[PDB]
Amino acid sequence: PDDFTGCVIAWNSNKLDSKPSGNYNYLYRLLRKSKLKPFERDISTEIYQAGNKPCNGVAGPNCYSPLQSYGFRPTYGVGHQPYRVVVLSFELLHAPAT
Image (cartoon, rainbow, N blue to C red; front, side, top):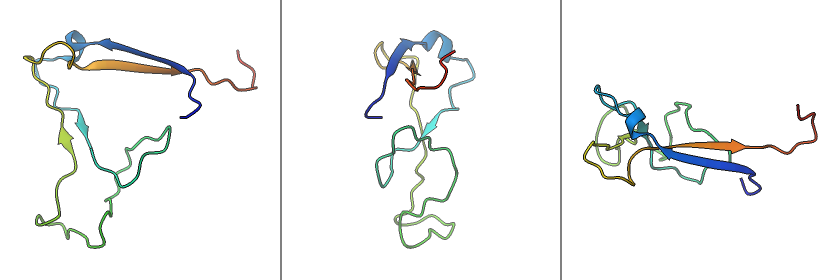
């Protein structure tokens, strides 16, 4: 948000985020019609009707899979390794602090 208050804490966790099985879990979408509003999470699975014509459940022109898997390898150097980030937002309200 524009008036965001808090602290961003980032640290490398490649020793912790690497497992012998493989980090196949993480996936991402890189396209959206409009910029996401502040403090918005995109997890709801609605078939995104970007165009005026459905793909009709078949592959073809102008119908590509949006989801992509992150490319992480042990040979990647320091600096691009997966960094864990915690955003601690300290909301300054008028309610009892406690």
